[PDB]
Amino acid sequence: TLSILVAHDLQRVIGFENQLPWHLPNDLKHVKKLSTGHTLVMGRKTFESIGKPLPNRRNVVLTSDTSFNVEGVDVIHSIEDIYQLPGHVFIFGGQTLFEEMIDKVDDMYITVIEGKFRGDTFFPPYTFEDWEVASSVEGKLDEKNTIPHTFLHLIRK
Ligand SMILES: NC(=O)C1=CN([C@@H]2O[C@H](COP(=O)(O)OP(=O)(O)OC[C@H]3O[C@@H](n4cnc5c(N)ncnc54)[C@H](OP(=O)(O)O)[C@@H]3O)[C@@H](O)[C@H]2O)C=CC1
Ligand SMILES: COc1cc(-c2ccccc2)cc([C@@H](C)C#Cc2c(C)nc(N)nc2N)c1
């Protein structure tokens, strides 16, 4: 499978100043569970905002930089390279890679953050007209997770 994995707010903001605008441990657990033992593909900027690969899965970074080399990270230089990666691949960000991949993926795991944040990077517009709701699950509010959020699994019609 080729999937998008993204968290976005009510206006499709995904980021501000190289960071996620919200702190939601439930969503990080969701990412962990979904992607462990599989492959994450991400743009160079997204990777550098974290600075370390995520343990226990393949970390793939797309960059034009022929010098790019980080321990625990595989590098690709073209979109076409994504289609050669085996197994379940998750397009993990950011704006640029989402824009390049949204028309190509089989499905999308979206966390909708029911808030309006200041952002400088956005998930591209999409219509439910193109996507079937395979599942929609409300995240639990609590002390450490205080923004309402919904886990959506969307599959291209
Ligand atoms: N809320 C969420 O779920 C998520 C949020 N984010 C956020 O996204 C933001 C970063 O987004 P954005 O600025 O778009 O950056 P990206 O992560 O998409 O990285 C852009 C870079 O990726 C490389 N790249 C993209 N396409 C190609 C290509 N076709 N060929 C070769 N290289 C390519 C280029 O690297 P180079 O310049 O080295 O050549 C480019 O400059 C951050 O704020 C982060 O917080 C990211 C993922 C999820
Ligand atoms: C190694 O590169 C990254 C690692 C993480 C990460 C690090 C620790 C725990 C969970 C995720 C997050 C990211 C950012 C850019 C992301 C994301 C993302 C999140 C946080 N939630 C959902 N639902 N989808 C995403 N793509 C990059």
Image: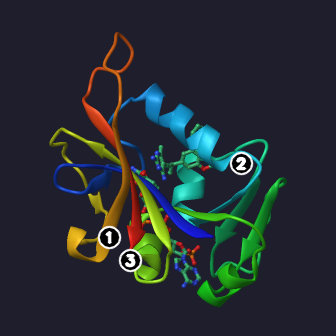
Q: Residues within 10 Å of mark 3 (few under 14, many from 20)?
A: some
Residue at 29% of width from left, 35% of height from top? 149
154 horizontally vs 13: left or right = right
Q: Is mark 3 within 8 Å of ligand 1?
A: yes
Q: Which badge, 1 or 3, comes first in the chain's sequence?
A: 3
Query: In which quadrant is the N terminus drawn?
Result: bottom right
Residue at 26% of width from left, 27% of height from top? 147
Q: Secondary structure at mark 3?
A: helix
Q: Is the C-beta separation of discs 1 and 3 under 8 Å?
A: no
Q: Is the C-beta separation of discs 2 and 1 under 8 Å?
A: no
Dot in front, 1 or 3 = 1
Q: Residues within 10 Å of mark 2 (few under 14, many from 20)?
A: some
157 horizontally vs 5: left or right = left
Q: Residues within 10 Å of mark 1 (few under 14, many from 20)?
A: some
Q: Nearer the viewer, residue 127 or 123?
A: 127
Query: In which quadrant is the C terminus drawn?
Result: bottom left
Residue under label 2: 53
Q: Nearer the viewer, residue 76 or 147?
A: 147
Cα distance in 3D space between marks 3 and 2: 23 Å
Residue under label 1: 131
Cα distance in 3D space between marks 1 and 3: 16 Å
Q: Which badge, 3 or 2, comes first in the chain's sequence?
A: 2
Q: How far across and down, in percent of the image, does residue 99 sit? A: 38, 77
Q: Is residue 68 visible?
A: no
- 102 in relation to 80, above or below: above
Cα distance in 3D space between marks 2 and 1: 31 Å
Residue under label 3: 99
Dot in front, 3 or 2 = 3
123 horizontally vs 46: left or right = left
Q: Is mark 2 within 8 Å of ligand 2?
A: yes
Q: How far across and down, in percent of the image, does residue 126 sit? A: 25, 72
- 96 in relation to 114, above or below: below
